[PDB]
Image (cartoon, coloured by chain):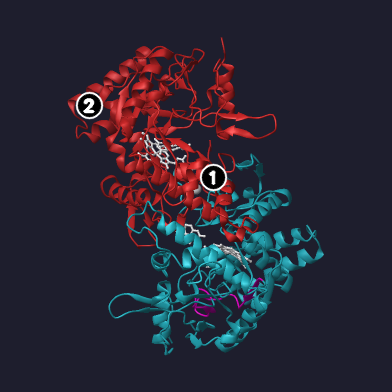
Chain colours: A red, B cyan
Amino acid sequence: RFLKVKNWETEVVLTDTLHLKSTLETGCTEYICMGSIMHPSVATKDQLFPLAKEFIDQYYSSIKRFGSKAHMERLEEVNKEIDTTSTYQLKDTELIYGAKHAWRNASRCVGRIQWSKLQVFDARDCTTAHGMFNYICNHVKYATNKGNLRSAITIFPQRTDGKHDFRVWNSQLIRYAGYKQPDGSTLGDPANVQFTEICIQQGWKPPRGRFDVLPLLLQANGNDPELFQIPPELVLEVPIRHPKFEWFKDLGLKWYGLPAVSNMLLEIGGLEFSACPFSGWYMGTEIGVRDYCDNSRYNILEEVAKKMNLDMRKTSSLWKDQALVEINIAVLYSFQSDKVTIVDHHSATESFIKHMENEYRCRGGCPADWVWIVPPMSGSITPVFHQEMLNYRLTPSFEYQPDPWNTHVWK
Amino acid sequence: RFLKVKNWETEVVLTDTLHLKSTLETGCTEYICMGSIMHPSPEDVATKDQLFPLAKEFIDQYYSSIKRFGSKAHMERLEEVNKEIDTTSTYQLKDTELIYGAKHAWRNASRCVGRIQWSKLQVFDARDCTTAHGMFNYICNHVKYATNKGNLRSAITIFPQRTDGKHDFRVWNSQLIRYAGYKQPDGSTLGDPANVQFTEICIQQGWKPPRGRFDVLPLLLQANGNDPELFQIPPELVLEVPIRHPKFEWFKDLGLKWYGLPAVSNMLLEIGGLEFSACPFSGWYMGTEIGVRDYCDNSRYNILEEVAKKMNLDMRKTSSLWKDQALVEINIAVLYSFQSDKVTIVDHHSATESFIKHMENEYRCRGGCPADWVWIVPPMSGSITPVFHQEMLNYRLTPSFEYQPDPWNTHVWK
Ligand code: HEM
Ligand code: HEM
Ligand SMILES: C[C@H](O)[C@H](O)[C@H]1CNc2nc(N)[nH]c(=O)c2N1
Ligand SMILES: C[C@H](O)[C@H](O)[C@H]1CNc2nc(N)[nH]c(=O)c2N1
Ligand SMILES: Cc1cc(N)nc(CCCN(C)C)c1
Ligand SMILES: Cc1cc(N)nc(CCCN(C)C)c1
Ligand SMILES: [Zn+2]
């Protein structure tokens, strides 16, 4: 079959053939859609062959060598390893290709126009937390690049029995701590209070401040995780100020310039890389709307609207909306002023529509999660809002996994 | 057999069992989701094996709503509907069943953020209508009733059901009250670009265009598959709010105004296998409907540019968020205007809050509530409204409102 999707702002129509190559569940059934559910629901020898063959098949097809001598030998070599070792090892080329295509296949990611420019750091030779610490430090120094950020991933040893997992317990490489006070209130980032407790428990001496960079809590080979403090010179940070409101700096906000997911799982050929931190650069609304203005986060909306002499009696005065825009002007202006790479939601979506059209043209489609692609503010005035999108799961993929503190058995 | 949905702002989990009674497909599969497609999934004059089981379902459903979970009346009604399909080739709905069906189509409207009011719906049985003149009469009564001098009331008028496909009753307007869109000689568009085609059909039918920016379109009404007829709504029946801004005194000098009564008049109301092609239903606006979409959409009124000019915004680049900032002010102006004129309007904060309460209510008493997150989340400030963080299950329950073809694609002109 073919499938059509339509832009209702422009009437452009694209024809998705690539969905015929989708695999694991969307979660949706023939009669129920779950597109708004965030989390819907080790491989044995038999289970691993078809996966390995499919990915090797797709890699050799991507390099115009399908059915070739080097293709058929690779397959046989992988088949050998899974009999010998119940698993197999990716070549370097397959690891780079796998990582890039897992980003390419990230339905929820609006930045995928950059997918082919990923720096892949092979860390599969790593054995200890300290070594992970060295890889991530280098990852951050590279990615940050004095403000001119560069996409990168670092991939650590794949799963084995599941009893020897590598994990970055941090959900992002750079995050700020949260501290719950005895009086209910929260100092710092409420999102990270639980993780802040875990670190404190593991010996972290916290500065109990408002923007404390958290420590890396790194697990290697299934051992208890260990604490490392990122060197402060490596953590690029941007004080937030406003181009019109001089009082804005008096909020004393800042944010880190380098966004980096670390809690996720990278599947390639049926091999699971449970520690694969990846970084890019920020869309302004991630900080400006969600990090600062979510009620379960830094929640400076009332603060910012208070200083904007806004009527906060009636919601219909739209103070929340007014204050949300200004905060997002400031976020953008601040990164741009300090020449730290950032992208506004308009430019990012405009670029995602181009990328999506190009991906239908050369690839047969582009899986896309409209619920995640549409920015969290000003939705309808961005072009993705009027763009129909099909959601399927292509592999290689990034996958969610359980939090390590829910699984790990301490020793 | 039992699915849960979770709110991420408040950690509240609801357990959905109502989806087990979902009837037809959503367009999705285990393999590919279409939750962002607008339309996923005349001889359809059923046989008896095709129409009776649908009818039997709705009557079974109605009689179980009313505690007569099987009874004398329910059994007679089945046999009455049975013989009716045998002879009249279809069947007619009792007045109660019709009111139940209309209220429940709205209840099951997965895209409708306003459904907490679903049971306070005025139903106007117009199944005795035979002509477009009569349709015009019934609609003028709807508009006046529902407008209620600014204290808007929900209502639906239900014209006779489809029979053979070639005797359809249709309202050709998409909403009862829409502004005209005119194709300018150079290439621009005056008025509302969404309606350029409908405006030309009306002009091609002899409507004399005043050619302003907010000309109210005439009703194009179709009865019994016959050609459609133009009627001008009486202007004293079309309430309009001039748009001014509580702070920007230069705002009213934009020459902007909108209508007060939103009325969808192009959907199909399906009950027990019966299809009501003409069923205009009205409520009141969420401000974002007018001021985000009607006013700011690129292929609509596109006034962001002009508002931003007067606000003195850095329009050099997007990262200034000059669009966003003007978007806020406009919606402020729209709410401020409807409320200053005591015309019913609901902001997007209040509306989404209410629908969270509605959802909880439906999971209490019914075991679920089908919702379309893509449509429920307002088109501005989405994440700062409670629904953005509210997981939703979507499924199709009957009775329901369905889309249908624009009648001019499919109409044999007498
Ligand atoms: C290069 C610039 C990038 C931009 C502008 C960007 C933008 C975004 C945004 C705004 C989200 C939504 C996340 C949220 O709302 O919390 C997202 C999600 C995501 N992105 Fe990107 N991203 C970029 C790079 C990357 C890279 C380099 C990768 C992997 C190699 C990646 C993979 C993902 C994944 C897996 C998600 C899903 C997040 C989740 O489900 O938790 N992205 N991206
Ligand atoms: C009473 C106040 C109401 C409010 C505030 C409200 C709100 C909304 C909104 C914001 C939408 C999305 C519209 C858009 O952006 O295009 C919608 C859609 C819808 N509503 Fe409501 N609504 C109300 C009344 C009603 C009534 C009375 C009915 C039925 C009698 C109804 C049935 C529907 C349906 C079927 C849709 C889907 C429209 C479509 O699919 O194109 N609503 N509603
Ligand atoms: C492609 C996408 O489904 C389409 O633009 C939808 C998105 N969400 C919407 N939500 C509402 N309320 N109204 C709409 O018209 C739309 N359009
Ligand atoms: C319930 C809903 O799925 C949840 O709030 C989602 C919606 N869309 C999102 N979109 C983005 N970009 N980020 C998010 O966290 C979410 N959260
Ligand atoms: C690589 C990358 C870039 C970016 N801008 N954002 C992300 C996701 C941020 C974390 N959220 C899932 C909480 C990842
Ligand atoms: C009855 C009703 C009430 C309301 N508040 N909004 C609507 C939306 C109408 C336009 N869209 C479907 C194009 C309908
Ligand atoms: Zn779906």
Main SS of residues in magenta? loop
Q: Between residues B106 and A315, which one lies in front from this camera angle?
A: A315
What's the chain of the residue with tag 2?
A
Residue A177 % position (x, y): 54, 28
Write down the quadrant of residue B169 in the picture: bottom right
Magenta residues, as a range?
Answer: B154-175
Residue B322 % position (x, y): 41, 58
Please state if B213 lies on the left or on the right of A309 as rendered: left
**Residue bearing mark 2:** A71
Identify residue type, mark 1: Cys
Q: Between residues B321 and A278, which one lies in front from this camera angle?
A: B321
Residue at 58% x, 59% y: name it. Answer: B348
Q: Residues within 10 Å of mark 1 (few under 14, many from 20)?
A: many
Please state if A296 lies on the left or on the right of B56 as rendered: left
Mark before the other along the chain sequence, 1 or 2 = 2
Q: Is residue B367 above or below residue A133?
A: below
Q: Is residue B159 above or below residue B37?
A: below
Q: Between residues A303 and B286, which one lies in front from this camera angle?
A: A303
Identify residue type, mark 2: His
Which label lies toward us, 1 or 2? Answer: 1
